[PDB]
Amino acid sequence: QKLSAYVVDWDLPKSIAWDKLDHIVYAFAEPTKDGELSGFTDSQLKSVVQEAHSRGKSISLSVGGWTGSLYFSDLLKSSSSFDNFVSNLVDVVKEYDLDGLNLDWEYPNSPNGVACNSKDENDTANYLKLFKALREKLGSKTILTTAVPTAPFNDENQQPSTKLDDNWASTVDAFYIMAYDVNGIRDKNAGANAPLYYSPKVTGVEPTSGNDAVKAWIAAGIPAEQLVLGVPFYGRVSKTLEPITASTGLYVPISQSSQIKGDSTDEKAADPCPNAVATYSGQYIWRTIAQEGIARNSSGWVTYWDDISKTPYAYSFSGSKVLSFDDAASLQDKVDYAKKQGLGGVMLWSLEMDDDENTLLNALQDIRK
Figure (cartoon, rainbow, N blue to C red):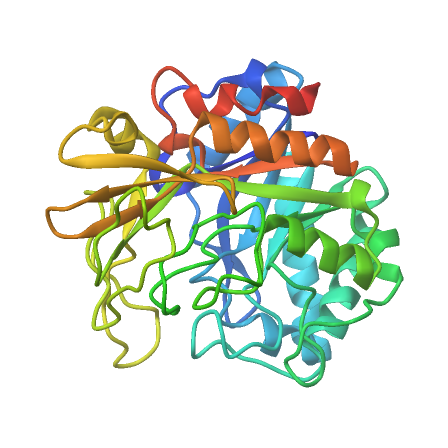
């Protein structure tokens, strides 16, 4: 699995380009309080598994997700709910003829991610117990992967680990680094959604990137070959308080009152926590970007290139907004990095975002390669 591609149950692609990929990750199954797997469509998963196997392709189920991470911590600390979760997790593999499971807990012991998510000092330790259980019960050929944040899983203090149990690398096959959503309204200045690099010279942005995350995880104990760079097929808009020109760069200050809306896929939504506030994400999928000609200086946009983060961005004087995103160029750069760093491969989120010409997916082909 050098090239993995997430598909979403709520929006399957009408046509999956099998020959341009290796491994399909079907998202999501959300764990319930009782430790059962839910929230996915039975017929669709059967359909997609069948297709993948017809063509000699691998498929995994992704358990969890941004809104599916509520019960992970509770489930694993208790011994009874642990075994039943595992039991259900094995059954689903059995049931659908899955080639593996992709655990996506967002995130172990963290006040970030959804606010009301259960959390515990031992979340990472138990996360490792879960994987070990899974391996014992599934064997060595089941693809066991995890989608991970830009720093190693939290310790008993909610700080990224400086060293992960060495059993992590020996149990789990690949760690999919979710190297995107790095910068947002949580920052003072505009930044890249999925930067390849971070520069300390630049303040008012988050001190991480793709390269930095890799570096962090390698240091924590995970070999590079077991690391997988996640890339987006979407971008994000911020509202700049100050207009971007050619003599300004990407890093201008932004509004923080409220996140403005992106494209038509960007519905106002609130996390599954009582009395939480609905918000926009700012998201703009690649399709919108391509159709509206944003990367071609159309529709009132002017396109630039950030030399620091190796990503394109665009600015509309109308509404004063900046769109940080990824194109063929920034994507092919991420692929160059991955190959030179001896990474296991790359993954993309998510397949239905790409245009009908497979522009973004094609830009990723050197990884297979």
